[PDB]
Amino acid sequence: MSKKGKSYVKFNMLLQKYILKNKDQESEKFLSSVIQMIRAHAEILQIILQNEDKRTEMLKNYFDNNFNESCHLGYTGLFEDIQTLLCLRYQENIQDYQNRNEIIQQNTILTSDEKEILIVSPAMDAIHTIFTALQFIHFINYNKD
Amino acid sequence: MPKNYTLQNASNLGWLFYKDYYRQEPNVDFISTQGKESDTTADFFRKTNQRITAYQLNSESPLVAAFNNHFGTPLQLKTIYPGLITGSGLPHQTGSKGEFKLGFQFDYTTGLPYIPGSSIKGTLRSMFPFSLKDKGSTKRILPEYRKERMEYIRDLIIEVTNINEISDTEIQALEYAIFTNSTPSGKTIEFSLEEKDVFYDAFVADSKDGVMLSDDYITPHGENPLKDPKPILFLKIRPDVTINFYFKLCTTHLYKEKVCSSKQIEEIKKQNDFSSSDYKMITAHQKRNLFEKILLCIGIGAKTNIGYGQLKKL
Amino acid sequence: MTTRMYVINTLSNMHVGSGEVNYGVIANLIQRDSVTNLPNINSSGLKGAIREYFKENEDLVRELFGSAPRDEKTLPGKVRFFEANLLSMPVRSDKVPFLMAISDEVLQELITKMKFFNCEEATQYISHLSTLLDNIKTQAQGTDFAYVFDPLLQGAIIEEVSIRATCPSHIPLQPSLKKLLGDRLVILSHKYFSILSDDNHLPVLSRNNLENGQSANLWYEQVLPRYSRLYFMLMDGNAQSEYLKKFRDTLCTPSTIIQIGANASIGYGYCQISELSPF
Amino acid sequence: MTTRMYVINTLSNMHVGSGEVNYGVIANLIQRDSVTNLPNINSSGLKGAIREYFKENEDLVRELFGSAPRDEKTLPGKVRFFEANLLSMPVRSDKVPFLMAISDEVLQELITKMKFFNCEEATQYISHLSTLLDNIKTQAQGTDFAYVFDPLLQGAIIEEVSIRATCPSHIPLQPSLKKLLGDRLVILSHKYFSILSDDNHLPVLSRNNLENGQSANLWYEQVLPRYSRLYFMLMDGNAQSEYLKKFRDTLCTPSTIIQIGANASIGYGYCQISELSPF
Amino acid sequence: MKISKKQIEYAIEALRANNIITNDNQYPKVFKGYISSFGAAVIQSGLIPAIIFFENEDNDANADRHKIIGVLKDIINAMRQQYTVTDATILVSSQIPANYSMAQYIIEHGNTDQLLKEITEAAVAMKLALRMYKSE
Amino acid sequence: MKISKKQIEYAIEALRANNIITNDNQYPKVFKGYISSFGAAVIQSGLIPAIIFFENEDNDANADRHKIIGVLKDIINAMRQQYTVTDATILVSSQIPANYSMAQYIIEHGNTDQLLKEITEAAVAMKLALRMYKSE
């Protein structure tokens, strides 16, 4: 992650919000089903992120339409927070890496394998960052009773 | 055998009307045009109809007694004479002379004439303001429909129960609780097992002295009065026949224009800010009286506009 | 003790929808067995209906049926519910209003199920049902048959002019088998019973949707005829004794009526559940 | 006294979940074999179910199955379990309620597996199955076939694959093969059995979750038809003979019913384990 | 019951051959109700009554109802033309005569389940085939 | 299976092209039920009857149900465009004509195993792509 922008701040706030504190008055009820949804729907999320004009609306609609059950009314805050973090991370990633990717691909000396090692996809990198943050939250929160 | 239906000596009336009606007999022809208009075919169908219309039902019928045991105390109403028709749209027609052209609603197992619970539920709901679905085609008549039906429901509720004043939202909530068992919207109310309104099948209860099925004619005269008429023969439930309506109704609790569960209303009553003015209760007996008034008003079955299916109190 | 056989007696026209799309006359069909193609109840539907009946007793439901969906503590249910298979179906006749119809294959399936599951009172029932089936097979000698055990039901037309009832005087019907299967019992061949229970012969109810008294929709619904009998197996999975006793007492009480299937508001699937009486 | 073959006879519908995310109509797909794509049970689930049945006898489980997952000391399992491959499946018919369906490729696979593993009674079964397969291939002459062996089952139609069965008179089916493969057995071509056992023709059931009468969820489940026959191989290593005898007696006792797969509370996956009978 | 694509093909050629479908792939709008009512009549009253009712030519109906029975006969003939040798031993594979009355054919051949099943499948095929074209 | 991103892109383009989604990323509510019911209908009935039912115009429905068949045809055409043209391959890459109803194409282009697989995959892609938008 890049500590330059508000993505780092939102990441820290998400960790603070959805990580359980020790018994003492209530937390924000982290949901673990979103972890596997992001992994499974990663390519669809990439398609949504690549849509510049309707990115936020498409992300919100996708999360609402996938998590459309009665239980999910309590996880609207989590959905909104992860949507904001994903959008911020994608914007930072494109700003940092777009021209770098174009110039790396246009280079003729570098081999294809080294090109693919050097080239990073902004949308997929942001999705992986969200996935790793949620996995860390779940790892801290869960205990084998 | 010929009368007094019972369970030991009878022929399934639905079976006779639908499957055994058009049985192929020697010397009887109704495939050809000549056969369909012949007097032999007319005699065959006359004998079949006479077999159909020869059965009576006793008040102490084990079938009706079993129905009473299973579905509770019935609501007994008596048929008046235009007759009574159910299941008129069922296909029963070949083109022959002396045959029943319209369909009839028979129970498969017992064979008795009956009115399905769906028919009763729809007939009762049709007199409630929110029976019509808000759709593109119905939006023209939608305001007048609800406006007319809400007044009727209001007077009927004030008549049957002690509630002096009822609001439009209260009527909507009561209707959606009785028929949909939900809120006006899509929300579900946590109801107990007994807090459900069930509309069972109305059965013919007792034909005192006489058969329960008779034959009737509707003879349309076309748009040309110079052409011949068209005699249509159908089967009807005879007048002076007792119809047993079975319901499973509960008590509806309305607090601040919303439908509440029994335990919900108990908790509401226990609270300090309980306004008795905002609490309304319609019991199962009052619901039965409301349904009885609706049935005595409009009736049930087919061709209700031209009189068929009107009921009187037994 | 562990396994008991319960008989379902329906009091109205019962519809457990299969939910599949039919592009023929009947828009809504009923559930059928995956193997025998006979009408049945899925064990999930039976368990859901019985859990709905007992929902008030939270402790009993939690111990017997399990935890409610999306509860924080997911604990498995102890009692195991098996699917209900068609035992007897009423068939229209000319000598009586309806007859209780069962096929030889249904009897053989019941005998095999009792052998495999080892019901509480299964020994005498298996013995007598095997004797009855052997007598029926001896009398039939490979042909189609419709055997009644009442001499007054000779020559009865079982829903079809082809099917006529003959009374074999040699074959006895034990009173307990009559109680289990039903009064006015007719034993049909597999072909006859399959014809009488297929989609072209099962009862259909016509429904229409009216908007301001004008018909908007129209469809036909397949139903299982009233007074039909279905049997299902209940397995006692080490459940607590007192809750089990309450469950069987409430279930087998004559005043108890349970709704199974669709169209509850219009009085469709109301049934009485009975235990296998000792022979 | 090693690597004997056991046959699984299902008393109800079996669902052993594959755990793969299907985004189509059937969210819950059953477990299928890696190479032949036929429905199967992994040896992990088989071992888990048999351990769950025997969990009361702690010493027998410890000796034969291994050690508890949270035991301080670990003990390897001495008995080797193998995956249960499908042997016979029920298919709908008109003359009979159902037929037992097996393919020539299924028979070839069974013969090859028995030859490789050398089951306890393998020699006679291999010889007779090879004779039957050779006769079937001689009669078929490379064409699609559906062969029944009871002369009364000639012209029986498979409903899903609308093909009527023919009776090859000169091909004999031995009584031990009848006991193994099942009664009313039809042997089809590979394509017919593949079509019968595919996802579109296996029984799919619709289920929902209701919250106060209104549907909260809806999903489609596919199941293995009741009375399906599966076979697995059981190898005993350096296991004690007394515990092995207790295990084999309890497992093959007619009163023993094992639950394999999901949906135990709604009577799914209940089966009986039978040993390979001497020819 | 699953309707095969060959049955729908047979229905299309039978509806063209009698004259339900015009050369511009259109049909009178009342044949939809005709076929639906025939299916309902078969399921409710029985095979013979429905066949007799819709076979009648001296009707007061707007269009030619008997052409649906003709389409039925053509579809059944096409279905029987592809019956396999082992099917012909169990099922009747004889072709229905063109000028023969369908009701009297059924009566003379009984009321066997084969004829009723064929009629139901062909009626469903006719409905599906009409659903593919425009109602005038 | 696993979600195919290219098929999701094809589904997005076809939903936009067949006038399902308005200028704002919004669609009539009943199309969700249409897409969901299409796959179940295909499995429970035949592919041909389901395509006939959904392709049927002049029906009594809350919206234009044939638009989903149009979307399916567009997605199948895009898939066949992207198909690799190599020998010893099974897939036929010829596009479905725009003057052709899908029912007619499947009727005269049988052995439709490839068509069945393509239709199921396109239905799944349609279902997953419709979740990016909002229902009015």
Image: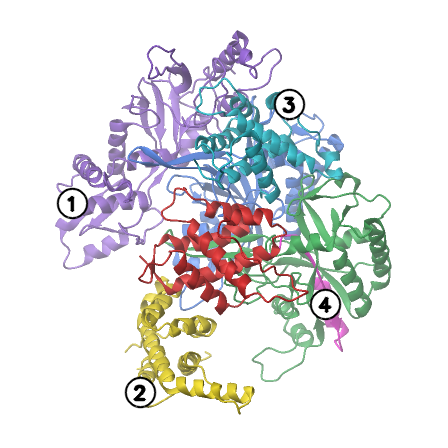
Chain colours: A yellow, B purple, C blue, D green, E cyan, F red
Q: Are marks 1 and 4 in contact (CB under 8 Å)?
A: no
**What is the chain identity of the residue bearing mark 4?**
D
- Alpha carbon of mark 4 to alpha carbon of mark 2: how far? 69 Å
For this rendering, which residue is in front, C144 or F6? F6
Which residue is tagged 4? D246
Which residue is tagged 3? E105
Q: Position of residue A117 (x, y in %)?
A: 51, 88
Type of residue at label 1? Ser
Q: Does the magenta portion include C75?
A: no
Can you say whether B279 is above or below E101 in the image? below
In which quadrant of the rendered image does the C terminus of chain C lie? top right
Whether discs 3 and 4 lie on one chain: the answer is: no
Which residue is tagged 2? A5
Q: What's drawn in magenta, residue-wise? A: D223-251
- Alpha carbon of mark 1 to alpha carbon of mark 3: how far? 66 Å
In the image, taking residue F121 as reference, residue D57 lies left or right, namely right
